[PDB]
Image: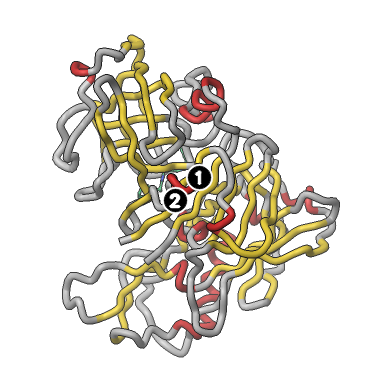
Amino acid sequence: SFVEMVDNLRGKSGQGYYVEMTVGSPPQTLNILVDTGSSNFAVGAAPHPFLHRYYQRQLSSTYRDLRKGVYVPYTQGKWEGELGTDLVSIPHGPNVTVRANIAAITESDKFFINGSNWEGILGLAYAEIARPDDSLEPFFDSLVKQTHVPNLFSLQLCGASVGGSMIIGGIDHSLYTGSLWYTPIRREWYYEVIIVRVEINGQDLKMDCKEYNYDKSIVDSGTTNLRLPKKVFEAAVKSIKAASSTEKFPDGFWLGEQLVCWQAGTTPWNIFPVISLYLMGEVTNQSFRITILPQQYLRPVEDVATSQDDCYKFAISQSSTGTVMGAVIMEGFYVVFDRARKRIGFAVSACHVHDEFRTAAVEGPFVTLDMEDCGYN
Ligand SMILES: CC(C)c1ccc2c(c1)[C@@H](NC[C@@H](O)[C@@H]1C[C@H](C)CCCCCCCCC(=O)N(C)[C@@H](C)C(=O)N1)CC(C)(C)O2
């Protein structure tokens, strides 16, 4: 019954992907942002200028207050609220209903986005990072523990405003081509992985592979960009600037604030390089790579000056808190979060990103020595 979940995600570019859910009794319908970078299920529960609707506890006969507060500070944005429980279901998901923890958001800061169509957040990562502490069982743990839904999910995030699929409980073989390559989940808190090699247009960055994972690398659908630690971001940008020196862009573009434009249909894709991330494999001394096209890290932005040009923002940004494989990296791949086997699988998506010459890829096997030395401590 996975066909029912195909195309159950929507979103706007740079504004995440959301799925429809219901909370309470009688059911209250809300759009919920799908976030593999956090572990709290939370929904707006008080008026807010950017909310079209909100969770009204006073109307749900199944609401149970927990007499406990909560706040979550993300990389950017934060909210606070009240903890409680209620019945939750996913209309275009498994045909079940679970009692789960819910944070009713009463105040927020730079969290809700003006005109985004979602009103809450579904953190799908592990208890270790739940707020206030790891005793607040996350939604997906509740789902698996109360139903027979198998302990895994897969995300097919599509670019161009955007759609996708979240298969809860398995893999839908019509959503990808080729082979699935698995990398171990290093530790169950974020979806942490180990990057063992980085190449740009086929040229190795020749860095201590510990630099790629300082102080961690994660798979995070709640983050738009590919976020790279200081030393890696500098090497990658320098490499990307040189490959595209044919044309000139403001330094505010390489800082991810200014947008570059071109005539409608003349974007010089061929001057921007492909980025290959090599990930630790399942077998000794074995890795595999995923190749990112520029159509992925040049995020198209809606120019409302003259809707006659193609404009983009550079979606690779600097980090001081580790590598983040954000939504633009996940886009065009089918990503399997195999919690049951502590591994994350990658395959070319059915909605893969098109270049009339190059293609995104997931290729292996590759031999890599001393992969364990690349994890940071
Ligand atoms: C568990 C939580 C406390 C936490 C704390 C730190 C933290 C993360 C999670 C990890 N995931 C972060 C992730 O969950 C958060 C979730 C967002 C607030 C969800 C709402 C906005 C979704 C649509 C616009 C995305 C813009 C974007 O890209 N935004 C807002 C990054 C900067 C971000 O922060 N997105 C990443 C990392 C580096 C490990 O840092």
Q: Residue at x 77, y 49 (%)?
A: 282
Mark 2, residues whose alpha carbon is within 10 Å: few (<14), some, or many (≥20)?
Answer: some
Residue on which the image places disc 1: 2
Instruction: Please state the quadrant of the image where ligand 1 appears.
Output: top left
Q: Residue at x 36, y 87 (%)?
A: 266
**Residue 300 visible in this rendered orientation of the protein:** yes
Q: Nearer the viewer, residue 96 or 15?
A: 96
Amino acid type assigned to the residue bearing label 2 in the image = Val
**Residue 127 visible in this rendered orientation of the protein:** no
Q: Find numbered disc 2 in the image and state the secondary structure of the residue it sits on.
A: loop
Mark 1, residues whose alpha carbon is within 10 Å: few (<14), some, or many (≥20)?
Answer: some
Q: Residue at x 30, y 14 (%)?
A: 62
Amino acid type assigned to the residue bearing label 1 in the image = Phe
Q: Which mark is residue 198?
A: none
**Residue 28 falls left or right of residue 209:** left
Relative to 170, say whether 323 is above or below. below
**Residue 78 falls left or right of residue 1:** left
Disc 1 to disc 2, how far (Cα)? 7 Å
Residue on which the image places disc 2: 6
Task: Residue 348 in the image: state x and y as whole percent.
Answer: 58, 63
Q: Nearer the viewer, residue 161 or 231?
A: 161
Relative to 116, say whether 65 is above or below. above
Question: Mark 1 and 2 residues: CB-CB less than 8 Å, in contact?
Answer: yes
Quadrant placement of the C terminus: top right
